[PDB]
Image (cartoon, rainbow, N blue to C red; front, side, top):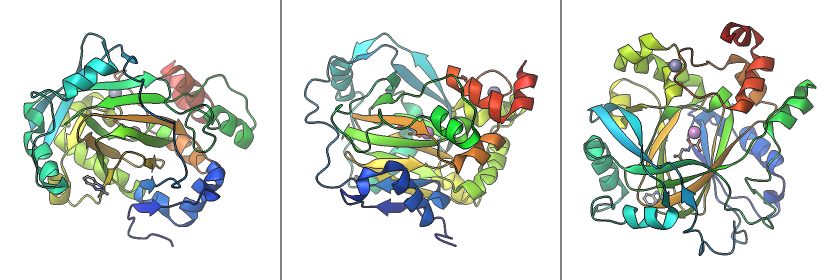
Length: 327
Ligand SMILES: Cc1nc2ccccc2[nH]1
Ligand SMILES: O=C(O)CNC(=O)C(=O)O
Ligand code: NI
Ligand SMILES: [Zn+2]
C-alpha cells in the first residue's frame, strides 16, 4: 500500500502533466496522496493564474465576518459576527493596521506558537465565501472556474441528471483568521489556490482516522454533541495540535504559500489559520472515487449548518432515506 504513514505529499507537475486535471488527480491517488487527507501541488514554473493582481481592490466583501472565540486556548468555538460591507482595498488596509497585523516573530514555528497561545484573545475579520474567481479566462490549466461539475460527474458515473451548479468562492484573510475543523459538504474533495499574500497553515487528519477526531470532539464539546449528531458540520470548533497530541489523534501539518494549490480528499478533516493578509480561491469537486463517500456522509440533523441548493440533489440521489426523513 502506498503512503501507509498517511504523510502529506507534495507534487511538482511539469507543464505537460498539468494539462489533464482529472488524470493528475488520479495519479496523485495512485501514489497514496489521499491517505493523508490533503496534498500540496506546486504548479509548473511557466504557469500563471493571471497576469497581475493590480486592480482587485474594488471587489466587495459584502458581509465581512468577525470571528469571536470562546473557551480555552487549545479548545474553543468561534462564532461569526456580521460586519458592514467593505472593499478589498479597505480590508487590506484594515489587515495591515496596528490592531490586526501579523506580530513580529522569529520563524513560522514562533508564529504558530503565538497563534495557538493568543488566538482566543482577539477577533480577526474574515472575507469568506465570496462567489467569484480571480483566474484569467485564458488560463486553461487548473482554472478553478473551468473544472468539470459534480453534477456532470454524478451523471457520468450514475446516469442520473440533476439540477444544480458548482462555482468557486474567494476568501480574503488576515492574521489569525481561522477555519474550524470540518470535512467538505457531502465529504467532497476541495481544491484551494492561494492567489496572493501571506501563507496559510493547514492541519489535517487522515480519512481512515476521521472517526477518532469525531470521538474526541464529542468529549471536548459535550453540549454541541448532544444537540446535533454531526455538529462539526457547523464549522465552529477548534482543537490545537497540542490537544490532538495529548489525545493520540493522528494528524499532519503543512503551510501553503502564495502560488500553490492544496487539495483536500473525501472525509479528510482539516483546519487552519492565515498568517496575514491573503486571498485564496476554492471550489469543491468529485471523482468516481468520491461516490461511496457521498453515500456515507453524515448530515447536520439540527438545522444549524447551511445546505446549498446543489447539495439538496446530492442528498436526494445518494441518501434517499435521509432525504425522506428531512421531509
Ligand atoms: C513550506 C513553508 N512553510 C512555511 C512557514 C512559514 C512561511 C513560509 C513557509 N513555507
Ligand atoms: O481557506 C479557508 O479559509 C478554508 N478552505 C477550505 O476549508 C478548503 O479549501 O477546503
Ligand atoms: Ni474545507
Ligand atoms: Zn447540526
